[PDB]
C-alpha cells in the first residue's frame, strides 16, 4: 500500500535540538543549576517520578532567546498543536541527558537492572567475535505538560 | 538482470561447526575439568555427572536438537566425515606422540 | 579483458583499469551495510569508463571524502551516471563537487536518487572571492552540466527554485536536454499554490521556456501536482510541444479533470504519444475511457491496482 507525502512547516531534528537546549539551560531566573537538570538529579536518585514541564518555562526561555536575538521557533505553539509527539521528544532528550544518581539505591534490587546487566554481559560475550532495550522499559519517570498561565 | 525470489534456508550440524572452538576443542578444554566420577557416588549420579556436561555442551553448540537426536547426528557424522576422522585420529596420534 | 562488470550483491556473509567501460554495482540495502568497491573506486582510476551505476550501498560516515564524492573525480568521460538508494549519500554534497571542479567534459545523462528526505538543498550560487583584490572562484556548474540529455532527480529533495536557477543560469543547456524526471521531490511547489516558502516554487513557465524541446517528462509520485497546479501546465502547453512521453502516475490527488483539460489543450498542437497514470486514485474510469474513445492519447495506462513504480532494470536499479 503506497502512500503520498507532503512537505510541512516543521522539523523535529531542529525542535529536538531546541528541546534539549531548553532542558540543559533553563532556570526560573526571574525569581533570583538548571531547574530541569536539578529535577532530573532528583529523578536519578529515584526520589521523584512525576516530571512536570511548565509551558510558562518554555515561554520564558523563548522570550530569553528572542531577547538575545535568535528565533526559538515557538515551541509553545508546537507543543500546543501536536502535544503527543513532543512527549516522545522530551523523554528522548531526558534519556539522552539525565545525570547519574547521587543517593545510594541498592541498584541490584531492581529486576530491570539485573536483566539488562545480564543482556549486556551476553552482548559482550557476542561482541568479542566468538538499542540494548526499548527505552520505555528503562524509563522510570512519567512526563506531563502543564499549561500556560493567564498572560 | 533479475529481481530475487526467496527460498527457505536450512541449518544442520556441519562437521566444521562441530570442529569450531566451541566444538570438540571445548570438550577437550572442559570435560576432564567438569565431569567427576567417584566411588563416593552411586552409578546413576555418576552417569548424570557425565550426561550433564555433554548435554550442556550439546545445547550450547547446537541448541536446536534434542540431546539423543544430537547424539545420533554426532555418531553418524563421526561415521562419515573425513576431516573429522583426521581430527579424531590426530587426537590418538597426539597421545601416541606423547 | 573485462569491459562491462555487474556485481549484484544479493546477500552478505562473514592502479589503472583502462579496460573497464561500464561498471554496475547493485546491492541489497538490507544486507550490504558497507560500500564494497569504495577503496578501489577512491584509489584507482578507470579512464575508459563510459557508464557507472551504483545502488543500495551505504556510504561510510567515517570517510568524509567518500561523502563528498571525492572518488568521483577519478572518472572523466563518464557519459552516464546513475546513483540510487545509497542511504548516506546526499545531493547536497554532490552539488558541491559540481560547484568546485570541472569534473567532467561531458555527461550525456545523470540519475541521482537519494532515498530519505535530507534538508532542503538549494543551488549554491554564492560565488565567494578569496579577497576583494583577487578573482572569484569559477563555479563549474555550467561546464559540468551543459551536456546533459537526461536529468533524473527522483526523490532528491531539490527545491523548485534550485531547478529554476539551473534553467535561468543555463547551467542546463535546454536544447541538449531532452528528458527530465523530478518525481517524488517534496520541495517542488507550483505558482498556483498559496502555502509555501517561496524558494520551493518551481516556475514551470521559466523552466519550460528554457528547455522547450524536451521529449519526456516524469512527475510520478509528485503529490504537489494537484489539479490547481496542473493549470500551470495547461497555460504552458506552447512551451512543451516536443513532449511525447508523460509520467504522472502514483499521484493520489490529480483528478481526471486536469488530465482532460491538459489533453484538450495539448490537442491544439495529433495526440500525445504516451501517458502513465497507473495507481492514481482520482482518474475516473469514464474519463479515461473517453480519453481513449476521443483518441486524445495514443496510449494511456490506467492500472489502478499497480501499487509500485520501480520496475527493476527498466525504471530503477535499486535491488528488488
Image: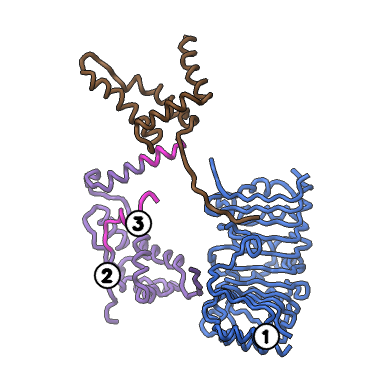
Left/right placement of residue A122 relative to residue C133 reads left
Q: Is residue C286 above or below residue B43?
A: below
Picture colour for chain B = brown
Rounded to the nearest angstrom, the CA distance separating label 3 from label 1 is: 60 Å
Which image quarter is the C terminus of chain A in? Answer: bottom left
Q: Are marks 1 and 2 on the same chain?
A: no
Q: Say which colour chain A has.
A: purple
Specify whether C298 is left or right of B84. Answer: right
Q: Nearer the viewer, residue C1 or A135?
A: C1
- Please give the residue where the numbered disc 1 appears in the rendered image: C296
Q: Residue at x 57, y 54 (%)?
A: B4
Q: Which residues are magenta?
A: A121-142
Q: Chain ID for label 1?
A: C
Q: Position of residue B42 (x, y in %)?
A: 21, 18
Q: Position of residue C235 (x, y in %)?
A: 66, 89
- On screen, C296 above or below A69? below
Which residue matches tag 2? A31
Q: Secondary structure at mark 3?
A: helix
Q: Colour of chain C?
A: blue
Amino acid at each position: 500500500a503506497a502512500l503520498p507525502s507532503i512537505q510541512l512547516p516543521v522539523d523535529y531534528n531542529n525542535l529536538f535540538n531546541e528541546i534539549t537546549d531548553f532542558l540543559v539551560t533553563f532556570k526560573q531566573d526571574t525569581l533570583s543549576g538548571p531547574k530541569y537538570m536539578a529535577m532530573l538529579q532528583k529523578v536519578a536518585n529515584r526520589e521523584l517520578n512525576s516530571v512536570i514541564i511548565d509551558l510558562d518555562d518554555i515561554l520564558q526561555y523563548q522570550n530569553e532567546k528572542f531577547l538575545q536575538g535568535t528565533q526559538a521557533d515557538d515551541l509553545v505553539s508546537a507543543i500546543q498543536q501536536n502535544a503527543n509527539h513532543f512527549t516522545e521528544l522530551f523523554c528522548r532528550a531526558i534519556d539522552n541527558n539525565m545525570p547519574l544518581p547521587t543517593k545510594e539505591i541498592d541498584y541490584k534490587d531492581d529486576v530491570l537492572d539485573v536483566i539488562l546487566n545480564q543482556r549486556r554481559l551476553r552482548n559482550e560475550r557476542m561482541l568479542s567475535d566468538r538499542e540494548l532495550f526499548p527505552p520505555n522499559l528503562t524509563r522510570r519517570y512519567f512526563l506531563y505538560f502543564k499549561p500556560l498561565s493567564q498572560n | 538482470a533479475i529481481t530475487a525470489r526467496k527460498r527457505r534456508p536450512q541449518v544442520k550440524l556441519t562437521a566444521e561447526k562441530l570442529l569450531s572452538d566451541k566444538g570438540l576443542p571445548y570438550v577437550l578444554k572442559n570435560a576432564h575439568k567438569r565431569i567427576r566420577i567417584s566411588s563416593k557416588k552411586n552409578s546413576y549420579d555418576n552417569l548424570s555427572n557425565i550426561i550433564q556436561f555433554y548435554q550442556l555442551w550439546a545445547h550450547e553448540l547446537f541448541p536446536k536438537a534434542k540431546f539423543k537426536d544430537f547424539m545420533k547426528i554426532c555418531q553418524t557424522v563421526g561415521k562419515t566425515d573425513p576431516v573429522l576422522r583426521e581430527y579424531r585420529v590426530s587426537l590418538f596420534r597426539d597421545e601416541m606422540g606423547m | 579483458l573485462l569491459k562491462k562488470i555487474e556485481l549484484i550483491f544479493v546477500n552478505s556473509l562473514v592502479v589503472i583499469y583502462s579496460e573497464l567501460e561500464k561498471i554496475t554495482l547493485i546491492c541489497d540495502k538490507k544486507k550490504i551495510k558497507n560500500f564494497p568497491l569504495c577503496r578501489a573506486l577512491l584509489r584507482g582510476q578507470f579512464p575508459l569508463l563510459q557508464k557507472l551505476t551504483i545502488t543500495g550501498v551505504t556510504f561510510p560516515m567515517n570517510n568524509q571524502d567518500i561523502m563528498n564524492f571525492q572518488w568521483l573525480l577519478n572518472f572523466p568521460d563518464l557519459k552516464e551516471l546513475w546513483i540510487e538508494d545509497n542511504d548516506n549519500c546526499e545531493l547536497s554534497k554532490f552539488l558541491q563537487l559540481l560547484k568546485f571542479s570541472n569534473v567532467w567534459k561531458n555527461l550525456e545523462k545523470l540519475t541521482f536518487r537519494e532515498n530519505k528526505l535530507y534538508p532542503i538543498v538549494n543551488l549554491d550560487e554564492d560565488q565567494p572571492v578569496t579577497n576583494d583584490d583577487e578573482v572569484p572562484s569559477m563555479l563549474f556548474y555550467k561546464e559540468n552540466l551543459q551536456n546533459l540529455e537526461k536529468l533524473d532527480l527522483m526523490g532528491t529533495s531539490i527545491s523548485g527554485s534550485a531547478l529554476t536557477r539551473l534553467c535561468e543560469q543555463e547551467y542546463l543547456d535546454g536544447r541538449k536536454l531532452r528528458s527530465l524526471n523530478i518525481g517524488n521531490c517534496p520541495n517542488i511547489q507550483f505558482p498556483n499554490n498559496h502555502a509555501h516558502t517561496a524558494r520551493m516554487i518551481l516556475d514551470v513557465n521559466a523552466v519550460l521556456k528554457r528547455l522547450s524541446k524536451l521529449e519526456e517528462i516524469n512527475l510520478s509520485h509528485l503529490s504537489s501536482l494537484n489539479d490547481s497546479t496542473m493549470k500551470s501546465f495547461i497555460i504552458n502547453v506552447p512551451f512543451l510541444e516536443n513532449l511525447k512521453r508523460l509520467d504522472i502516475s502514483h499521484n493520489f490527488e490529480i483528478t481526471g479533470i486536469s488530465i482532460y483539460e491538459f489533453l484538450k489543450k495539448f490537442q491544439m498542437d495529433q495526440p500525445l504519444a504516451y501517458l502513465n497514470i497507473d495507481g492514481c486514485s482520482q482518474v475516473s474510469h469514464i474519463t479515461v475511457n473517453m480519453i481513449r474513445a476521443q483518441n486524445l492519447v495514443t496510449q494511456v495506462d490506467c492500472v489502478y491496482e499497480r501499487d509500485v513504480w520501480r520496475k527493476f532494470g527498466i525504471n530503477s536499479y535499486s535491488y528488488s
